[PDB]
Image (cartoon, coloured by chain):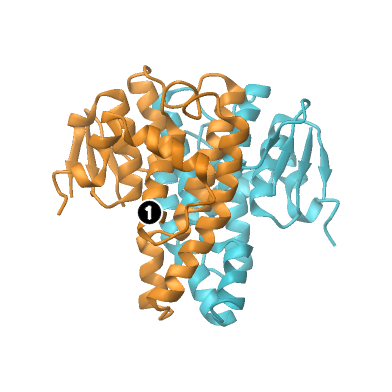
Chain colours: A cyan, B orange
Amino acid sequence: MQLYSFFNSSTSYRVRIALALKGLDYQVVPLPTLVDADGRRFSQSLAIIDYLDAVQPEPRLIPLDPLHRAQALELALLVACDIHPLNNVRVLKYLTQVLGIDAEDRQRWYAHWVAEGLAAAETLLNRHRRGAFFAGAAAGIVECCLVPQLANARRMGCDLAPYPALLELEGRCLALEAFQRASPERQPDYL
Amino acid sequence: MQLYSFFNSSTSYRVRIALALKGLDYQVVPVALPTLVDADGRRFSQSLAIIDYLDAVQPEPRLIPLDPLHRAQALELALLVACDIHPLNNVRVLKYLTQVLGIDAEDRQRWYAHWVAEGLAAAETLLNRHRRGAFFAGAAAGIVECCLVPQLANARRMGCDLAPYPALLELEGRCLALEAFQRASPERQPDYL
């Protein structure tokens, strides 16, 4: 398979993590678009992560148990639907060039959606985590979504002190070769 | 189970359609929404997590396909709406644009219509290229129609041009002809105007 990836795309980071956790090799093509062995194209990171679970079930990125699965998807969709979309490069571009919102107002916009969303993420992780990772002994869709969100929030100057369990989970993920391999800074298109 | 719904919430509408397709819409309860509340008082948020959970609660008729390829295609279109359109066009976001950045109704209008045009052009193409049947997944409505019908009602109400999406308009018409969608509609809610 091929992944049309950019090193600094949060959605590409999500899928590079999932591919690294499966141990699947693919060809980065410097979004995202996964092209499978049949030439089918997929661009929505959370659909790709679900599909990878069909392509190579073990290790599993989304739980089988219906309640554990609902809890994992709840936290993944909080990130994918209620934080990231508002803070996209395309949205900040629109705010500057079309509405002329200055760097500082764009900061406060960025920080407002992060603060609301990460407070809820911290709550859900503390409530529903089953072990070292959200799903127990292995990282999955929750870590695929939280790790890029935290990197983005950090880089935009957000206060992350109110989210100690998110920061702890982030550290347990960034200690793993799979996350290190997927990281922006280790990508072939990275300056 | 109970579903805490507001008549005018798009994400509530998505889950009221899902419940109506299952034949469980006695569970709906008027006035972040929606919230599904089970037997033992467990609260589920996230409209797409709730739709997925309803397939565990009562598998038939299925809102998310079993076949992996068909599932990836249905989730691609559903997530296009739920991730790339609706979150930018939320009441919550439009309040921030008004009350914080002082953007007028006219610039708000144009923001709404930009994310709508970008998203629905891509949605029209996915529907045309990947649909399995009269509905996206086949002969029955599912997660794709649960996301599209609320998004088209919203776009129409905000004055968006929907002429460029004839396949989306046709699918919307097939859904709104069904009793399950008519029951789920905002206009038929107990809390409606």
Residue B39 sits in which quadrant? top left
Nearest the viewer among B181 and A184 is: B181
Query: Is B108 left or right of B178, judged from the image as shown?
Result: right
x 59%, y 61%: residue: A88
- The image shows residue B23, relative to residue B109, as above or below, that is above
Q: Position of residue B187 (x, y in %)?
A: 21, 46
Q: Which residue is mark 1?
A: B154
x 36%, y 63%: residue: B92
Q: Secondary structure at mark 1?
A: helix
Q: Position of residue B90 (x, y in %)?
A: 39, 59
Q: Position of residue B182 (x, y in %)?
A: 26, 36
Q: Position of residue B71 (x, y in %)?
A: 55, 27
Nearest the viewer among A178 and B115 is: B115
Residue projecting furthest to the top: B60
Nearest the viewer among A104 and B26 is: B26
Q: Is residue A7 visible?
A: yes
Report the chain holding disc 1: B
